Amino acid sequence: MLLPWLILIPFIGGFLCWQTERFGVKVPRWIALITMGLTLALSLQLWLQGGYSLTQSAGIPQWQSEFDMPWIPRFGISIHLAIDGLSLLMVVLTGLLGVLAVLCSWKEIEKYQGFFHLNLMWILGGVIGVFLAIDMFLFFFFWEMMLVPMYFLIALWGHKASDGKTRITAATKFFIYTQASGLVMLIAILALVFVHYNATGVWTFNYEELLNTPMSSGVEYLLMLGFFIAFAVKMPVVPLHGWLPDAHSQAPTAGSVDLAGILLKTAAYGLLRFSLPLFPNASAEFAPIAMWLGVIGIFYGAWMAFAQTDIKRLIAYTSVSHMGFVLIAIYTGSQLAYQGAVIQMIAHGLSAAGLFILCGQLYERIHTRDMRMMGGLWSKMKWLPALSLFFAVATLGMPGTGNFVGEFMILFGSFQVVPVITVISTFGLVFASVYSLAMLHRAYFGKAKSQIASQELPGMSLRELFMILLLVVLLVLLGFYPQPILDTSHSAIGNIQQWFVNSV
Amino acid sequence: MNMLALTIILPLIGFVLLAFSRGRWSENVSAIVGVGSVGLAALVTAFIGVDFFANGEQTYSQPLWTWMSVGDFNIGFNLVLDGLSLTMLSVVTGVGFLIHMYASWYMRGEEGYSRFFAYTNLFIASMVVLVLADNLLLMYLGWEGVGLCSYLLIGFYYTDPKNGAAAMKAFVVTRVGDVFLAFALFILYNELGTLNFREMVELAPAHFADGNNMLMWATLMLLGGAVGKSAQLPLQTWLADAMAGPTPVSALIHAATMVTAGVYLIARTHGLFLMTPEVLHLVGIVGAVTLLLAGFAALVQTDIKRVLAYSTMSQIGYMFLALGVQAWDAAIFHLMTHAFFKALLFLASGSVILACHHEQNIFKMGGLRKSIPLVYLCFLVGGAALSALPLVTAGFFSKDEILAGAMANGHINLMVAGLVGAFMTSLYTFRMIFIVFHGKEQIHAHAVKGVTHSLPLIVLLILSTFVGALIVPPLQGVLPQTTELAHGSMLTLEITSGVVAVVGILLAAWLWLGKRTLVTSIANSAPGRLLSTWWYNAWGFDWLYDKVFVKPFLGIAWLLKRDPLNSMMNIPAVLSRFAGKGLLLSENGYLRWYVASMSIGAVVVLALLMVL
């Protein structure tokens, strides 16, 4: 019921901001803040009003709210929006990140600003629609239309048409690397539906009847690779992640909040929801390749993070290290491991968003991007580097932050299922420390005479500090007290694991 | 009595105030609130200590709230106040109170004031969490809680980057130990299910009827965690560099707060180490080889802070031996004495280096008895206890008891290790004060008189002596494995340690009382400098631990200065663009070749149809 409205407010707000662009220019900032407030209101209403602590073994079909509507009846394509417990965590996270995106874009007036915000709400609404998606075509359409408006963001707002490096390399690799694999998973969807159409005799694009379709061995394996390729180019996996640092280092850091904190979520959401239950034996065969790619991703991202000299590419290469833990979590037979991935995933968004906001904040203070050029700014800034120290501290497994409990319950479940690949995996924490300290010492520890421009520094406004203070206190409560959201996700995680166990 | 969290909340809450009053408060109000947080902590500790005496040494547990709970993974904020944990709380809430009360006077006159009293409270709060935790998880929060605080206090002065760069090697090394510590934590949950210490104690033998081979991996890798956080061979790197910070943080890190976490983990899991005897004796094996390393490096360099540091390394490993010889209560007795002397010994040195006015040398000062004898009596009391002197010292009973236990274990190499350690402690006992305080004062050390530090000096003077040795720590509430006692040979071992201490003290005084030309000759002899350079490298261990992984890490970072896999999956675009440019060049514009294209399409279509 609430789901059609909850995916449509982003699109309605873009229309109204661009409508009132003719009326005024200070309107869309204040319009956008209220519209994202309504998005979190409906999302938090579903958290509180709904039975978040529901039955742990109520089957694979279980939803607090559900919407159905005929869209293309010839294939049974329907607007099958349906919200689960873990999907509701995703919706509340993106509503909060949308508030941060529209708050960081405050006091940013240009030649056109309504165009920026209709695009801003369009891309955030696309991610919400992926998170509420049970029909395969609706899932794919939303997956691919959140991908078009970021291209305009990197192009027309990466820099205003002055340098050609903001389109022809950064934005173009971002677009092609995702869309080729999106078309791969579309033909994977179609091969799965056609083998189901031979089995039963109805053209259906719905998840519940495609869940248990009879397929011979050696056939569903190729479709599982087809799903995983599109789910491995969106979250950074080892062979195909070259788009991520270019995308984050060129887009404005509000666009980078969208590009890191929430676009990385949807691929592991799809690995939990759409790839694991549909292909149980194929995923059981593919598991060790996934573990090898996971350990390679953690070690690889940390080394490339240590070796880099700038900051946006630095945090962009932390992200590929973080997601390796999540991939190994998903491809195991443990309930605790999956519940560790969820808390690690929410904390991943919350620990990347603050760093990107602050890295963009530091650049507009000093007008210099290279990290090794500055140094010793602690005597000049009064609140930026202290808050930045805790966010760099929250990146690695420091307890009292959500990242520690996240990565570390994965390791418990991972050692429960398989010893040797887990005992390799744990060493990324040592490597997490070295790139964390490298960031901290190269940027803030030292003498302010490392740069001439490090001798005249501005002040920090109240609202940026307010939205940084909220994230640090929110992230500490998730580290100390993670029970409420684990009780929320228990049943959804449990039936996925029980199906992955029982179907093999 | 329902007041355990007040030993954590009251410090921790005070940190939050000083973390946001970033220098806007004045000197006095900031000083009072910083000391009063730790003062309330000691008072609440004393109330529960005297009530623990009223409890009849009965443990009191308090669960605040469950942390996380999955149906097979139950972790809760459980606090256990038993005899072992009460003693480890007593050291912290007294020593941190005394060290921090000195910092109320030492810190004033310079900036970074509210900042320093913010991070000290967090440092103390993390150490209290570690020793009161009942679950290995919550205790893990303690380990890297105090590690991050050591980073924030070693690199406290952010202006010059030497001390600003010295902290991260400690941070990297302590997280290697924490990875080693969490490895055993995974294995214990896989093998025995519950992480509570007592439920673990009488669940371990029930689950272990069949297979035992994997428990040595758990316990050996658990041991690798304990050793690293304080000081030991496999990971002894950072304690020389930790001296680059201010004097009060060196006392807190090195004396009794952070370095007393690796002792608490071995002691708390003593039954768990009794499940496997060889991993228990291996603690003493590594302890016996580190007393041979940690001693004479105090003599080598001319830095007073490096002197006090290699002595702490020697003493902590001396404990590991004491725990490896199944003398548990005696080791904590050694800790109860050890906290008192080391903190004062470190602190008094700071007062005089305030008076030194940027000297930082041991060979250019002398005749300091006439400057101020208060610091003279401070080093003196500390030296006597360390050397195992029988004259009204506090710690000599602890050394006598652990060597009695060690010879009751019956390991002649361990008594040889103990004998050479007693001789080696007496060597660097008085050599420092003889080379520094005796001679001629060509640079005057201006002494500073003030009651604000004199009163804690008198308190630390009356506490570090044998008057403080009469306070028996609570050890009857845990009922550990009983420290065995020997009679008849107790007097023989007592006089043997006294003779060893006296010979070492007389040799240092004979080094002093000579011309020192032979000392200069052995400080100029080429094999002497070879050993000095060899133990500058400290068995090459910092040398080995840098050149084994560091420049490979920098080399792979220099190979990762540009991202390889982003480039190597761009070759589809490279091939497509170059192949597209070739196809554009294939077009001509001359219409004869257009018709030739039509004929050559007809030729290939007919050929492709005739092969079908």
Image (cartoon, helix red, strand yellow):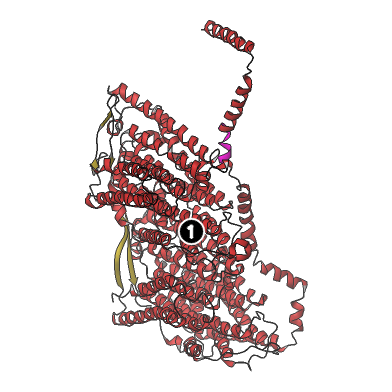
Residue drawn at (77%, 83%) of the image: B517
Q: Is residue B119 above or below residue B587?
A: below
Residue drawn at (62%, 53%) of the image: B554
Q: Nearer the viewer, residue A304 or A349?
A: A349
Q: Is residue B22 above or below residue B434?
A: above
In the picture of the structure, the residue carrying the numbered disc 1 is A392
Packing grade of label 1 (10 A; few <14, some 14-19, many >=20) is: many
Residue A187 at x, y = what percent? 40, 27
Q: Nearer the viewer, residue A296 or B360?
A: B360
Q: Amino acid at mark 1?
A: Ala
Q: What secondary structure predominates along the stretch shown in magenta? A: helix
Q: Is residue A168 above or below residue B251?
A: above
Residue drawn at (61%, 58%) of the image: A373
Q: Is residue B507 visible?
A: no
Q: Is residue A269 visible?
A: yes
SS at circle 1: helix
Q: Is residue A268 left or right of residue A458?
A: left
Which quarter of the picture shows residue B79? Answer: bottom left
Q: Nearer the viewer, residue B334 or A469?
A: A469
Single out the residue that lies furthest toward the bottom.
B370
Magenta stretch holds residue B569: yes
Residue B466 at x, y = what percent? 48, 88
Range of residues picked out in magenta: B565-572
- Where is the N terminus of chain B found, in terms of image quarters? bottom left
